[PDB]
Length: 174
Length: 171
Ligand SMILES: [Cl-]
Ligand SMILES: [Mn+2]
Ligand SMILES: [Mn+2]
Image (cartoon, rainbow over all chains, first blue to last red; front, side, top):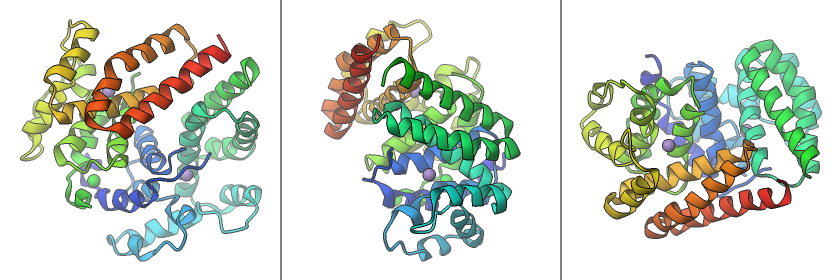
């Protein structure tokens, strides 16, 4: 019963800045779904769940006032550090960012990236672009599968089943 | 904006009872997310959204776990009951009943619940199931969405069209 005592709502509030935005899906729902996936797999860690609610807020909001994170509570500093670990710097090679997370990322960053990827892989279900589904499937297999194998075998199984399912859709349709 | 002052985590705790079955836990949290997305910042509704399928999907569920949380737990329980189908009840007549007698909040909650379920059809293949679910959504939930929230109607519309388009372009 440790989850009852985690004050998440202020991090949800911050995440509402994303309401009205799409990345190939709905960025706000994606933050809350990422948190749901972490709780689903039994990660009840204050900093990780809090970071999960705003992990894309720095990346996807122009001129985002980082003090909106840092002013919330005594953990806001550890939350900010975790969000930074999974924020891609402007212009940085996506390949090298993912490679960098597996090499130097904390346990929590790796877990967060896996949950982020599960949520994004589920959102491919409503896409049609076809070439996008394939590139995203390949990226997930090459770079995220190994992260999931380090931190959580069950997360690896879900990522596996989602990649197989989407590749199967390409082959039976687009 | 009033979101900071809403005591949500204890209702999330309750929702973790659903971890294990079909994904019902994710569905509760996604339903709450959809409500926040559409700008519903109402204590009772967001709280109900986190546990709306707990009574429906857990046989011998100790309702006191809900009623002991806070001063609103009674209003939350009543809202959950409005969108709970009784053990033997015609699905048709339950949906008809929600549009006839359901509160504004029950109707909104059902729309958000349906949006979330319609998004989860994206990983299904059963084909006959997709069609029945699409038809059920068009006939019984579209009109609910038209009463309470036009934007929710547009999302339910686009999801039904998207899934029907999939059926037509393969099996
Ligand atoms: Cl909370
Ligand atoms: Mn993300
Ligand atoms: Mn439901």
